[PDB]
Image: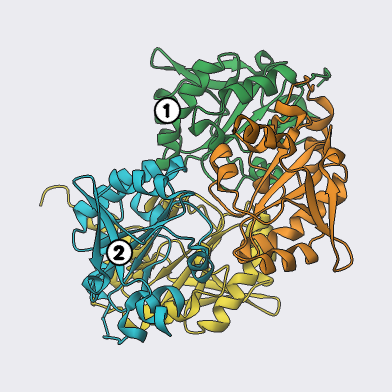
Chain colours: A yellow, B cyan, C green, D orange
């Protein structure tokens, strides 16, 4: 009751209200509610890291086999210029350009690239999916994992899935 | 054929400094942890402590050693310092090919119906942070029963 | 041309105060560049291997290249370690130069800024490496160079 | 009786193998005296080792006198042959080389190790090194600057020393 800082906390209800993507030469926004109830693939990467650039071929093959999983780029670029040139050469959504070490701390991400597969209720279906997707042996078994894994509904703070996923 | 019908009909273990065998049908309907390793590889020997802590946390998962020892005597000395089950001493590169196993140790978590629950579990179980995530995977993954060729889940799991 | 301004001091904690050292102290020394962060548990567990490395190679100066998110996290790291550190800043440009893609990473650098061991973090986790590294140090001819951190981190 | 068997190892690894014209050829191991070597631990059934060949070809272009030797972990002679025909590397004869993995604690395929003429390890984890563009000038400096102190190999057999603890 004393020293209630709900007022301060409430700013976070609009955290990550948009993701970004390229269409022709436009950096466009998409309302993050679009990702409600979707499986996500979180791609931790940077345009300056050659391994992350070669990894895009594996992600593109993954996307062809798992078209309903949405790929979200979590950038570790140095400038907007680097971020924008990379995003325009991909079919991915992205977090806005920013410093995301706090997400690395939450999931103990220690390598670029890293790729994690996330269920609609923000559980981790595959922690180390970057390794998983560089051969093609994974496809049938990942389809079984997605088909068979029960999704128990959760309540996200402020009804904000990305606040839950990246902060809580 | 004939030894298709008898492929992997027993797994092996040590007890009281004696090599023993168990009907492999005992592993029907069990979660398995396939431990790819070798006694010559120091990273595999230290990994035994992570597996033992894993087993304490997940006691219904059966740990099966898939050996890459050079000699039967090295295999035996390794198996006697563990309480794991093991495939018979043999050359298992065909299993490495099937699953694209490229590192020792590797550890794969398998459901009762031979699906892969966690492909790269060695790195998962050396941390502190995996228990609740793995508990949820096991509790949430629906098991549809399967019948296996030659009535032998290891024929399916290792040879298709 | 304030390249003269670049990396004039490294930092460290001693007697619970933040101190600085002129970067010319590191001229002609073997260096161990430790890319790390206090938020990364694997970097924190790696400090024990670095301390054992330092006991066996006391003349190699370990330099911490930070990837902490905040200045307070960086200071807490310095208070708990015995390395010299770059000032708190964003060092992705060094990661790009050397294609550092993992934390921790550890690189061993000769007095004239050549790379003696590119991927030394896995090397020093064991203690199998010690004789091999002693031979590399003993046998690597040094051709002296006039300048060191602008050459090492930018070129 | 078998102190004579121990002497047999003076002829250990007397030939390496390679393919030139879909044709299997042998080369006297003495060709490799005083050479730097790149030991490539790999297997044709391992997709990561197949993709690694691209990095080894860039390495061979930039370091043509570092002789690449394939240490096989193929299941069958035919897998070994097909791999060798497509990479025209030198190779140990098809066999089981777990004892080499024990000596050097090789735990990943592919692995690649750079060896000096006196059998010291110049770069232990060279598979990681050569996947980047950046390594070339500093590896040339490392080869140019590392002093080679002469050693005596048992039976004057370099590969016996390099592979057999």
**What's the distance in space between the residues labelled 1 and 2, CA to CA?**
40 Å
Horizontal and vertical percent position of residue B123: 41, 53
At x 75%, y 48%, the residue is D69
Please report, as a chain letter, where disc 2 is located.
Answer: B
| Other-residue count near label 1 (Cα within 10 Å), few / some / many at <14 / 14–19 / ≥20 | few
Helix, strand or loop status at disc 1: helix
Horizontal and vertical percent position of residue A80: 64, 58
Please report, as a chain letter, where disc 1 is located.
Answer: C
Horizontal and vertical percent position of residue A89: 69, 71
Horizontal and vertical percent position of residue B110: 33, 69
What residue is disc 1 on? C48
Residue at the far left: name it: A1
User: Does any portion of residue C39 appear in the rendered image?
Assistant: no
Which residue occupies the foreground of this view, D140 or A39?
D140
What residue is disc 2 on? B11
Q: Residue C28 lies in what quarter of the image?
A: top right
Q: Residue A27 lies in what quarter of the image?
A: bottom right
Q: Quadrant of the C terminus of chain C?
A: top right
Against C145, is B133 above or below? below
Against B9, is C51 above or below? above
Q: Quadrant of the N terminus of chain C?
A: top right
């Amino acid at each position: 009751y004393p020293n209630d800082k709900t007022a301060e906390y409430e700013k976070y209800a609009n955290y990550m209200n948009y993701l970004y993507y390229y269409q022709n030469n436009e950096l466009k926004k998409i309302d993050s509610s679009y990702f409600k109830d979707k499986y996500l693939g979180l791609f931790f990467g940077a345009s300056w890291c050659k391994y992350c650039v070669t990894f895009i071929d594996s992600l593109n093959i993954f996307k062809k086999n798992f078209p309903n999983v949405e790929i979200i780029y979590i950038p570790f670029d140095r400038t907007y210029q680097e971020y924008q040139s990379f995003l325009k050469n991909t079919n991915f959504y992205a977090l806005p350009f920013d410093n995301y070490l706090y997400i690395c701390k939450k999931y103990q991400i220690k390598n670029l690239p890293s790729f994690m597969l996330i269920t609609p209720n923000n559980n981790i279906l595959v922690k180390d999916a970057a390794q998983l997707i560089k051969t093609d042996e994974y496809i049938n078994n990942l389809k079984s994992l997605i088909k068979n894994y029960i999704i128990h509904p959760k309540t996200f703070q402020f009804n904000n899935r990305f606040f839950d996923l990246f902060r809580n």
